Image (cartoon, coloured by chain):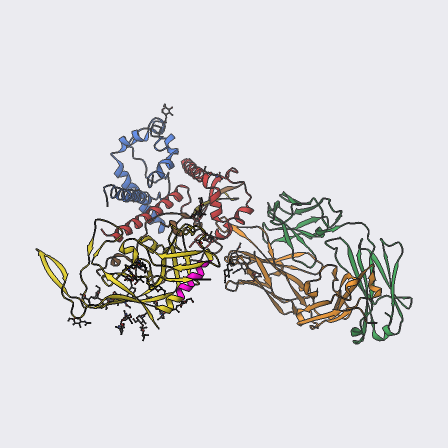
Chain colours: A yellow, B orange, C green, D red, E blue, F brown
Amino acid sequence: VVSTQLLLNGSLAEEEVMIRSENITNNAKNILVQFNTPVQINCTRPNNNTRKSIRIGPGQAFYATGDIIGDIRQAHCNVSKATWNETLGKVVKQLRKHFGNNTIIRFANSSGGDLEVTTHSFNCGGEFFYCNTSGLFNSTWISNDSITLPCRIKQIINMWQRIGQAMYAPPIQGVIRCVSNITGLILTRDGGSTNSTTETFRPGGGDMRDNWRSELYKYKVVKIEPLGVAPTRCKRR
Amino acid sequence: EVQLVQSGAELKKAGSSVKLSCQAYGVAFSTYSFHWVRQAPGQGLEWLGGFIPLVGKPNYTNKFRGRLTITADESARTTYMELRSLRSDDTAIYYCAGGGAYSSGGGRFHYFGMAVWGQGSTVTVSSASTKGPSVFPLAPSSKSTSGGTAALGCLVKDYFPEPVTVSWNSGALTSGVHTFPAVLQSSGLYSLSSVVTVPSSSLGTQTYICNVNHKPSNTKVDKRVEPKSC
Amino acid sequence: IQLTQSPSTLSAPVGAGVTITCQASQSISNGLAWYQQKPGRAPKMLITEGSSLKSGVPDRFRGSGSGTHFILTISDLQPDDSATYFCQQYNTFPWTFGRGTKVEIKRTVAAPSVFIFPPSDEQLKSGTASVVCLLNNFYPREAKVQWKVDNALQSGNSQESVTEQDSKDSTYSLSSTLTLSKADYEKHKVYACEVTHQGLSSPVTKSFNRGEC
Amino acid sequence: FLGAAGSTMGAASMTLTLTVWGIKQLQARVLAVERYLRDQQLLGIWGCSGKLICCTNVPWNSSWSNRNLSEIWDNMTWLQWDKEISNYTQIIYGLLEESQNQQEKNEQDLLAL
Amino acid sequence: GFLGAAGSTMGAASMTLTVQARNLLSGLTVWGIKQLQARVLAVERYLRDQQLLGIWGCSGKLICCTNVPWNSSWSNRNLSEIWDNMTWLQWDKEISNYTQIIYGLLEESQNQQEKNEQD
Amino acid sequence: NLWVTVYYGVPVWKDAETTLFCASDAKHNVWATHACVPTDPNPQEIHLENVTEEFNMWKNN
Ligand SMILES: *[C@@H]1O[C@H](CO)[C@@H](O[C@@H]2O[C@H](CO)[C@@H](O[C@@H]3O[C@H](CO)[C@@H](O)[C@H](O[C@H]4O[C@H](CO)[C@@H](O)[C@H](O)[C@@H]4O[C@H]4O[C@H](CO)[C@@H](O)[C@H](O)[C@@H]4O)[C@@H]3O)[C@H](O)[C@H]2NC(C)=O)[C@H](O)[C@H]1NC(C)=O
Ligand SMILES: *[C@@H]1O[C@H](CO)[C@@H](O[C@@H]2O[C@H](CO)[C@@H](O[C@@H]3O[C@H](CO)[C@@H](O)[C@H](O)[C@@H]3O)[C@H](O)[C@H]2NC(C)=O)[C@H](O)[C@H]1NC(C)=O
Ligand SMILES: *[C@@H]1O[C@H](CO)[C@@H](O[C@@H]2O[C@H](CO)[C@@H](O)[C@H](O)[C@H]2NC(C)=O)[C@H](O)[C@H]1NC(C)=O
Ligand SMILES: *[C@@H]1O[C@H](CO)[C@@H](O[C@@H]2O[C@H](CO)[C@@H](O)[C@H](O)[C@H]2NC(C)=O)[C@H](O)[C@H]1NC(C)=O
Ligand SMILES: *[C@@H]1O[C@H](CO)[C@@H](O[C@@H]2O[C@H](CO)[C@@H](O)[C@H](O)[C@H]2NC(C)=O)[C@H](O)[C@H]1NC(C)=O
Ligand SMILES: *[C@@H]1O[C@H](CO)[C@@H](O[C@@H]2O[C@H](CO)[C@@H](O)[C@H](O)[C@H]2NC(C)=O)[C@H](O)[C@H]1NC(C)=O
Ligand SMILES: *[C@@H]1O[C@H](CO)[C@@H](O[C@@H]2O[C@H](CO)[C@@H](O)[C@H](O)[C@H]2NC(C)=O)[C@H](O)[C@H]1NC(C)=O
Ligand SMILES: *[C@@H]1O[C@H](CO)[C@@H](O[C@@H]2O[C@H](CO)[C@@H](O)[C@H](O)[C@H]2NC(C)=O)[C@H](O)[C@H]1NC(C)=O
Ligand SMILES: *[C@@H]1O[C@H](CO)[C@@H](O)[C@H](O)[C@H]1NC(C)=O
Ligand SMILES: *[C@@H]1O[C@H](CO)[C@@H](O)[C@H](O)[C@H]1NC(C)=O
Ligand SMILES: *[C@@H]1O[C@H](CO)[C@@H](O)[C@H](O)[C@H]1NC(C)=O
Ligand SMILES: *[C@@H]1O[C@H](CO)[C@@H](O)[C@H](O)[C@H]1NC(C)=O
Ligand SMILES: *[C@@H]1O[C@H](CO)[C@@H](O)[C@H](O)[C@H]1NC(C)=O
Ligand SMILES: *[C@@H]1O[C@H](CO)[C@@H](O)[C@H](O)[C@H]1NC(C)=O
Ligand SMILES: *[C@@H]1O[C@H](CO)[C@@H](O)[C@H](O)[C@H]1NC(C)=O
C-alpha cells in the first residue's frame, strides 16, 4: 500500500500503541506509530465521469475525459471524531513516556514541501487522491459527528520520488467510493531549543521504505550451518 | 533451574502395589535422564532404575526384576515408578533424580551422574492403620530457664506412619530449634518432641506457635505454647 | 561392580583436611561422582567425572584418581561439613553406590543445658503423662540420663532420641521422654533427671513437684 | 527444525535427524542444489557419508579447546561452541581429509597382498 | 596446493587426491548471465562424474579396486616404471586410446556382480 | 585420549543476505502475483525455547 502521513490496510499492535524511532532524541528521524485498533475512513469521488477515445496514430488511442453528467462536486474523505480523539489520547499517553510526565504535547499540520508530502496521498480504485489533513492534526494536550477532509485529484503522476518518468492515469467512469483502516502514523518533531516545555509533532512521509519497515520489523534472515566437530572418547574402527 | 517435584507419603500393606510420580520443570523432558534411588531407614543409597524418555528402554537392577516398572508421560512431564508385591523391607524413602547425557553415535550414551534430586516420598509397608497425632505443649517454666534462656516446645505423640513436619511461627523461628528424631513406641505409634530456646524476656511478649502437619492422616495442628499459669 | 569406602567414620577438627578413599572392584575409567547427604535431606552432588567440581560447591572439596582408586579431599573442614559422603559409579549399568563415610566435627567439650518439662494438662486429660528431659548443646555425643520418681530409679519406661550434630556449633542435643499412666503420674510427688556428661564435673539434677510451679 | 537451539550440546546430539519473480525463483533453486551438493561432498571426502554422527581418526589437539567433557556437553550450546573453535575449523577439515586418504591407501595395501 | 603435484610421480601424486577433489564444485546484464550457466555447468559435470563412479561400484571412494584384469594389449610396461618413472599427465597420453573399452568392462562387471549377489 | 567427532545437523546459524522469492494465495495486476509460487495452507512455525536474538528494525536488508 503506497500512501503518506497515514498507514492503511496494515497490521495492528496486540497490547498497546507502539512508538518506534532510530534515535528518539534526534529530531531528524521519523517516528513510526502503530495503532491498537483501526480507524475507519470513507473516501469518495462523487462525479459521474465520461470517457472518450481519440485516435492519435495507427493503432494508438488516448483516453480523454468527456462531460460530467449531473452536477460537479468535491471529492472528500470522512473520519470519526470520537475515534480519532481516543486514538490521539492513547498516542499522547504512550508518547509521554519519552518526554516526561508534565510536558505539553501539541499536534499541528504539515509545513512546506511538495504536494505528495504535505497531503495524505493515496490511490482509490485507479484514481489518485491528495487530501488535506489539517483537521486531523490540530490540538493541544496538557498533563456521531464526522471530520471531513477535502481532496484533490491529479492525473499526471510522478512516483518513487523520481524525475524523468511521468505516468498518465486514464479516467475512471462513474462514482468512486472506498473504505479503509488507518492503522498507524509517520510523525516528525520540531527542534525546540531554549528550555522548551512543549513538543510539536507534524505528519510526515514521502519515502516508501518507512511504509514497509512497519511490516518487516519482526523478521530477519539467517543462514543454517548444520555441520560441527566436537571432542569425544571414541575412535574409528 | 531444573526442579523435580515428588508425590506425598504412602502407607501400603504386604502384597499390594505402590506408584510414585515425579514431575520435571525447566528442561526438555525427552532428552533428560531420570533415575530412582531408594534409602532404607539407617542404611545407604540404592539405585533402582534409570531411563531416558526418548530412547524409552528402562534399565533395572537385577534384585528388582519383575517387580519394578518405570514409565513416562511426556505431556505431563512426569515419570512414574510402580513397585509390586511389597514386603516389610520395602519401607523406605524414594528419591527421583535427574541428569544429562550425550551420544557419540551408534547406540552409545555417556552420562554425568544425578545432578538434580527430588525431595523424596516415604513409603511404609505395614498392616497398621493411619492415626492422627496428638500435640501437647511443653510449656516454659522456672525449671526450664537457664541464664536468661528458656526452652519451650511441642510433643507430638501417637501417630502412624512417618513422617511429620514441625515448624515454629510458620517458619519464622528457626534459630535454636531442635526437632528430635521420631522413636517407635511399644504401641507401634511414633513420638517425638520439637523444642526451641528463646530469651526469657520474650516469653511475655512473643507468641510461640508450633505448626505440625501429618500428611498421611491429613492432620494440621497449630498449638500455642505459653508459660504455665500460676 | 562393588565400591568400597574407607573409612566408615571420621572425626577431625575445623580447618583440618580429611581424605576418603573409594575403591572399585573393576576399572570404571572416570565415571565416578561424589555426593554429600545431610540428615533428613536429599543427597547433593559434590564432584563429577572424578575430579570436576560442580558449580556452587566450595573449592575446599577436591577429587582425584582413576582406574580403580579415587580420593576425595576436604582441605578446610567446617562445622557445616558433618554429613555422609558417597561415591557412585555411572560408567556401567547397574549404577552402584558406596556404603558411605560419616564425617563428624570434633569440638571442645561443652556441658549440656538441662531442662525438664512436666506433662501438660491436655495430655493428662487423655490418661497418659509424658515428662520430657532436654539436654541442649553438649559435646561429645555420649551422655547419661537417669529418671527418678520419689527418689526411686526408673527403668524400662523411658525413651531417648539424639539429634544429629548441629551444622553451626557442632553440638548435640538429647530428649528423654518418660511415659506413665495418669494414675501412676498422680501417685508420686517429685520427678527428677540426673545428667552425667564429660563437660560436667558432677551430675546435674533437675526436678519438679507435681502440681507445683 | 532448529528446535534444540537453546538446549545443551548433549541434548541436541540426540535429535540431529523473464519476469521479476521468475528470475528470483531460479536463483533460489540453483542455490539450494549447490548447498546440498557441497555439504554431501564435504561429508564424503571425510569417509562420513551416510551417517549423522561419524567417528574419525584424528586426535583432538588441546590448543583448540582445553575444557573438560563436562563443561562442553553439559554447559554449552552449539552456538556457543561455534564461537570458540571458529578459527580452527579449516585446520581440522584438512586433517580429516589427509586422514581419510591415508585410510584409502592402507586399504589398498591390505588388498594388495 | 591445487595441482601442485602435477609434475610428481604417479605414486607421490596418489596421496593428494583430496586436494583436487574439493576444487571441483565451488573452488540480466553482460556479467549477469555469464555467472549462472557457469554454476549449472559445474554442477552437471560433477554429477556426471559422480554417476560414472557410482555405476562402477566405486561410489564415495577415492581409490577403488575392480574385478577387471588388465589386458596386456593396452600396455606392457611393468609397475616399476609406471608408479616411479611416470606422471599422470604422461600416463594419460598413452592409454587415451583404450579408455572406453575399460569403462564398458567396468560397467558390465559391476552390473554382473550386483545381479549375482542379489540372487 | 580424545578424538574429533563429526555431527551433521547441529542447530547453528549466522546473519546473512540472500534473494527471497514470492509466494501468493492461489489476471492483469501491477504486481504479478500469478507468477508466484502457491502458498502452503498450514505453514509450520517452530518456537525456539531459551533463545535470545538481536534484531534491528532500521538495518533490515
Ligand atoms: C483497503 O482495503 C479495502 C478493502 O479491501 C479497499 O477497498 C476496496 O477497493 C476496491 C478498489 O477500488 C473496490 O473494488 C471495486 O469495487 C467496484 C465494485 O466491484 C468496482 O468499481 C471495481 O471493479 C471494477 O474494476 C476492477 C479493476 O480493474 C475490474 O477488475 C472490474 O471488472 C471492474 O471494472 C469494470 O467496472 C468498472 C466500473 O464499473 C469499469 O470502469 C470497467 O471498465 C469495468 O467494466 C472493484 O471491484 C472494493 O469494493 C473496495 N472495498 C470496500 C469494502 O470498500 C481499499 O481500496 C484499500 N485501501 C487502499 C488505500 O488501498
Ligand atoms: C528455559 O525456558 C524454560 C521455559 O520458560 C524455563 O523453565 C522454567 O524454569 C523455572 C525456573 O527457572 C520454573 O519455575 C519454577 O516452576 C515450578 C512451578 O512454578 C516451581 O518449581 C518453582 O516455584 C518455579 O516457579 C518454570 O516452571 C519453568 N517453566 C517451564 C515451562 O518448564 C527454564 O528455566 C529456561 N532455562 C534456563 C536455563 O533459564
Ligand atoms: C541521538 O541524537 C542526539 C542528537 O539529537 C545525540 O546526542 C548528541 O550527542 C553529541 C555527541 O555525539 C553531543 O555533542 C550532543 O550534545 C548531543 N545532543 C543532545 C541533544 O544531547 C545522541 O548521541 C544520538 N544517539 C545515539 C545513540 O547516537
Ligand atoms: C461524509 O459526510 C458528509 C457530511 O455528512 C456526507 O455528505 C453529505 O452531507 C450532507 C450535508 O452536508 C448530507 O445531507 C448528505 O446526506 C451527505 N451525503 C450522503 C450521500 O449521504 C458524505 O456523504 C460523507 N461521505 C461519504 C463518503 O459517505
Ligand atoms: C463509513 O461507511 C460505512 C459503510 O461503508 C459506514 O458504516 C455504516 O454506518 C451506518 C450509519 O451508522 C450504519 O447504519 C450501517 O450499518 C454501517 N454499515 C456497515 C457495513 O457497517 C460508516 O459509518 C462510515 N464511517 C464514517 C466515519 O463515516
Ligand atoms: C496548515 O494550517 C495553516 C493554518 O490553518 C495553513 O495556513 C493557511 O493557508 C491559507 C492558504 O492555504 C491561508 O489563506 C491562511 O490564512 C493560512 N492560515 C494562517 C493561520 O496563516 C497552512 O496552509 C496549512 N499547511 C498545510 C496544509 O500544509
Ligand atoms: C487545508 O485546510 C486548511 C483549513 O481548512 C486551509 O486553511 C484555509 O485556507 C483558506 C484558503 O485556502 C483560507 O481562506 C482559510 O482561512 C484557511 N483556514 C484557516 C483555519 O486558516 C489550508 O489552506 C488547506 N491547505 C491547502 C489548501 O493546501
Ligand atoms: C478494518 O477494520 C475492521 C473493523 O475492525 C475489520 O473488520 C473485522 O474483520 C475481522 C476479520 O474478518 C472480523 O472477524 C471482525 O468481525 C471485523 N470487525 C468488525 C467490527 O466488523 C477489517 O478486517 C479491517 N481491515 C480491512 C482491510 O477492512
Ligand atoms: C528500545 O529498547 C531498548 C532496550 O531493549 C533501548 O535501549 C532503546 O533505547 C529503545 N529504543 C527506543 C526508541 O525507545
Ligand atoms: C452515471 O451515468 C450513467 C450514464 O448516464 C448512468 O447510467 C448511471 O446510472 C450514472 N450513475 C449514477 C448517477 O450514480
Ligand atoms: C478530545 O479530548 C480532549 C481532551 O479531553 C477534549 O478537550 C476534546 O473536546 C475532545 N474532543 C471531542 C470529544 O470531540
Ligand atoms: C508519568 O505518569 C504516569 C501516570 O500513570 C506514571 O505511571 C508514571 O510513572 C509517570 N512517569 C514518571 C514519574 O517518570
Ligand atoms: C484548529 O482548531 C482551532 C480550535 O478549535 C479552530 O479554531 C481552527 O479552525 C482549527 N483549524 C482547522 C480545522 O484547520
Ligand atoms: C579468532 O581469530 C580472530 C581474528 O584474528 C581473533 O580476533 C580472535 O580472538 C580469535 N579467537 C581465538 C579464540 O583465538
Ligand atoms: C621435481 O623433480 C625432481 C627431480 O626428479 C624431484 O626431486 C622433485 O620432488 C619434483 N618436484 C615435484 C613438485 O614433483
Inspect the magenta stretch and tell me whether residue A168 lies in it. no
Nearer the observer, D110 or A227? A227
Whether residue B108 appears in this view of the structure is no
Ligand 1 - quadrant of the structure image: bottom left
Nearer the observer, C99 or E28? E28
Q: Answer with left or right where residue B64 lies relative to residue A202.
A: right
Q: In which quarter of the image is the N terminus of chain B?
A: bottom right
Q: On the image, which quarter does residue A145 sit in? A: bottom left
Q: Answer with left or right where residue E53 lies relative to residue B40.
A: left
Question: Residue C95 at x, y = what percent?
Answer: 61, 53
Q: Answer with left or right where residue F1 lies relative to residue A157.
A: right
Question: Residue D76 at x, y = what percent?
Answer: 51, 48
Inspect the magenta stretch and tell me whether residue A87 lies in it. yes
Q: On the image, which quarter does residue E31 sit in? A: top left
- Residue span colored magenta: A86-96
Question: Residue A182 at x, y = what percent?
Answer: 34, 63
